[PDB]
Image (tube, rainbow, N blue to C red; front, side):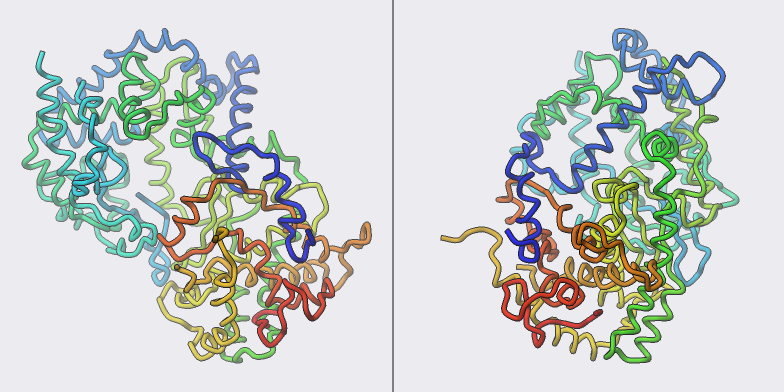
Length: 626
């Protein structure tokens, strides 16, 4: 109706007046439309790779003609057991624990965690992360959820296939996964990954698991044994077991599972007789997804783990002109700065908090803008027609790519987490932030349209990563990663005394027509927290100049328009409105005009009157950052 009242009723429902919704998924919108053009065009690149007549001359062209593997599946059927039987013969030759652990470590290189992260007090401990997980099923819980076992009505039928060896597989194959479905910790603990921190030496990891070689395995995993001596063990309650399984679970008890796991490690694109057999376990019986994936889903569904930072270099070259880099170089130099200067005209902070809130912003960073460094992939060699051992080696250094990044630093522009995702997170330990360019793609960011709308809608969602990067919880962390509220509670209480309305407001609103974790307002502090700076660093980007006053609509009025169109998201929200309390987060549908109320930069911008609906009276507004 009226933009200041509902921009997303003024603009955004018309997509929802017309748009489909997927029968297989039943959700589509902001992120998923960026998964769409992420997925819809990466196919076009390999099509362009295959369209080109690449005969010889580069080591990167049979990579881009690897897709001929998936074409003639009658061809790929003819190999079948023989490449596998080599992979069996690795295992069949592997007699002892050391022979197997060193055997499978190369298979593990061939690609059936880590982040380059120091302690944030030590600037140096860039190591790997080791927890417990081995369940073929979605989580360990399906063992102990004894009532959640009608789901197992035909599970051991569609997996025990590989006269009686299938039966003795069926004796074997149900027997251990229950024991793999035991030692592993609750999911939502991992969705706020908390107790992983045990900064171990690998001298500890050899001491950790009794009965398994944790090192010559790792040399078969291909890391630095001498030159990288430490890790982060997280949850070794299985890892100690696993080695004791490696002690006690015998090789024949391992083997036909390990072969079942090995074929699972190369499941989909192989001899066609057995590819639906795991799908009809997984697709039709574990998920009931009977849509046999069309090929353009399939061939795209593998390349990224095979090659992470490979397409994205020429992807932006084959999609985006050079116009978009100066947009970063002119914008975000101001945003990371002027967020400091937004602290200034806050006229009630504490000086020991204000100057502290200033001083934390000559030091702050951004993994945004053309990556300075890129991982080489042409010199990584992949056949046009071979696929199986072709991508073993293709995966083999995919382990050891990150090995080098144990030695290499965060150079601030290469995207450790992949460019082609739809992700965003601040590091409460390291105080880095991460923005893969799906959020920086259009329609979020047009690289050639007007600036302030392309500035507007994005910058508070950036600033909400800052604003939730600087929540009370973001404040409860330190710049060196220590857990401490520098933001002393006496303002937070007064700011809770200002934001008492924010505790209460969504309770006066209804998720569904009528005929519990709203105690947290977590998604909404930082968007007002981010819009605080969306309309300030612009002026630092102006250096006091006037924003582009075009069509009777200035940059600030256009910064409204940056947000006013860019939330068209459709679904059926019975489960969703029912799903809300698994974590106390908030949705976007209440968010999409919630920040009209307490802000004042919009009212002075748009001249809001003293009685309106999305007007809020100033004694219940909150001049946090305005």
